[PDB]
Image 1 (cartoon, chains in turn yellow, brown):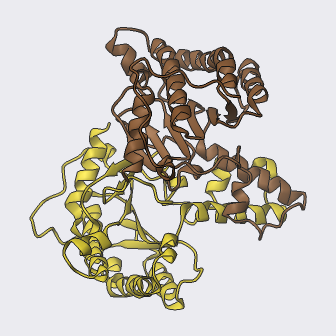
Image 2: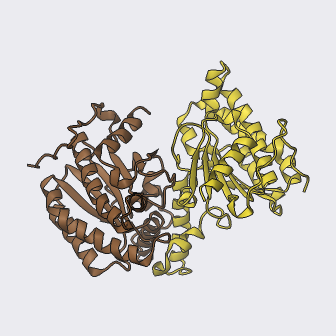
Image 3: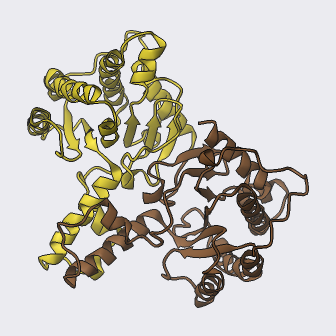
Amino acid sequence: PIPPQPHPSGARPPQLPRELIPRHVAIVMDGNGRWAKQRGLPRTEGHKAGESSLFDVIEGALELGVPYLSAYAFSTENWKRSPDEVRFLMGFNRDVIRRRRDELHARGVRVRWAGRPGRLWKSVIKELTEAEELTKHNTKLTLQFCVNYGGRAEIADAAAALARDVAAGRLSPNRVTEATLARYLYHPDIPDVDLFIRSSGEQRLSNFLLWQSSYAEFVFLDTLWPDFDRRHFWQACEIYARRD
Amino acid sequence: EPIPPQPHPSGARPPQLPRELIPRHVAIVMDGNGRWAKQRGLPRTEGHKAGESSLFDVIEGALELGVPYLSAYAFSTENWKRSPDEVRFLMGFNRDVIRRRRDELHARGVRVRWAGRPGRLWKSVIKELTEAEELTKHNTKLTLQFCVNYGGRAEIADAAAALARDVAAGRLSPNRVTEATLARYLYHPDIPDVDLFIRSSGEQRLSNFLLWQSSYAEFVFLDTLWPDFDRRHFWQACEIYARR
C-alpha cells in the first residue's frame, strides 16, 4: 500500500496506546452550506471544499491506524432540499468517487457503499458499485461511504431480509434476536461505531448508523466540515482516549 | 380532574416558551448516583435513593411546562459496569419506587407505560409495573415511559421477532416490510419520536436507550449529577432545545 501524504502543517498523528485508538469512527460532514454563507461563496463551493476534508481525514485514519471510517456523504434527508441542490449533490458525489477511486485503491482503502439505490441516478449507482468491486480485496482502511442512507431504512431492510428467510423456512421466528437482525445489516462484517464525530455545533445522530452507534462515544466539534482535516479527527480520537 | 403539580421549594416557575418550541417527548438518562454518594462518603445505593426525588421533581417540571411524553432509563438490562449487589438493589428499588409513587402519579394524571422485557426480572417487579400500568391507563396529562429491563437494540429485535411471527403465520408479506411496518411492532408504537434526549452527567453517549425513537432527537449533555437534578435542569434543557 502507498503511504498517506503527511499534512502541509507538518502535524503528526498523536502517540496513543493501540487499545485506546477507536476501531470504527463515524463522521457526519455538515456545514458545507453554512461555511459558504459565512465566506459569501455559493453553497456548491462548501461541498467542493468538503471533498478535500474527507480525503485529508482518510489520510489521518491511515496514519493513526483506524481500520474503519464511515462518512455520511448523502442523507435521504437531502430529498427535502431544492431540485438544483439535489442535482448538484448527485453529480458531485459521483464525480468525487470517479476522480478519487484510484488514489483510494492505491492507499489500500476498501470502499463499501451503504444505502439504497432508490431514486439515485444510474451513473451514481454505477460509480459506487465499480468502486466497491475495484477495492473489495483492500484491508488497510474500510471507508463505509453512506450514499442515499438512513439508519432506520437500514434496520427496516435488515428486518425485511430476515422476514424473507422466515417465509422461506430458512429461519425460525423464535430465533430472532439482536445478533440475528445484525447479520442482515448492509455490512455486517463492519463492527460497532466506537467514536461518532459531528463536525458542526448541531448535537444530533441525524439517523446515521443508528443500530451501530448504540454504545458509541459522541464528540461534537465547532469546525464546519470544509475547515475539518486530520488534525480535528486526531483531536476527536484524543478526546475518545482520555475518556478511558 | 387532575390534581396540579406541587411547585418547587425555590418558587422557580416554568419558562414562558411558545407551545411550538416545547418538546413533545423528552428522554432522560439518570447518571451519577454513584459519584454523588462517593462525594458525600455514602454507599452508591444512597445516590439511587436520592435519584427517586430527582425523577419525581422532573415529572412535576414536565406537568408544569406541558411536555406530554417523558421517558426515563430506570434499569438497563446491560449493567456490565455495576456490581451484582448494586444490580440486586436496583431491581428491588425500581419496584419499591413504582409501588410508593403510583398513587401520587395517578392523582396528577400521569399514565405509566412499562417498556422492557419480562426476561430475568423478578415476578414482584413485573407485578408492580403491570399494576401501575392498569391503575393509570386512562390518564392523558403526561405519559411516563418507565424503561425497566430495557435496551434499544432489544426493542428493535423484539419488533423484528413479532413482525417475523406475523410473516410465518401469513398475516404479513415480507415485501411489505418498511420503516412504518417495523415501527408498529415497538413496545409502545403510539409514543412518538424523542424530540430532546437529556444525559444528566458528563458522559456523552446514547447507552442503547430509545435507539429507533432518538434517530432525529436533540442531545443535551448537562454536568449535574442525577441526585442534584430537578425540574430547573429539565427546564434549562428545554430552553437549550427551543433556542435551537
